[PDB]
Image (cartoon, helix red, strand yellow):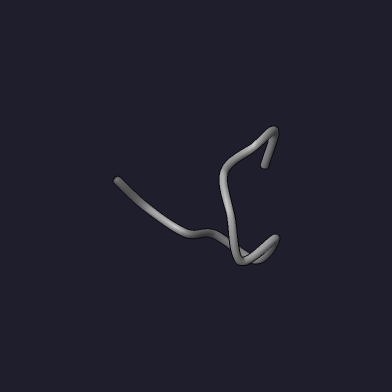
Length: 12
């Protein structure tokens, strides 16, 4: 689990 710049890896 990692929350990138999109604050959520739904497609980021």
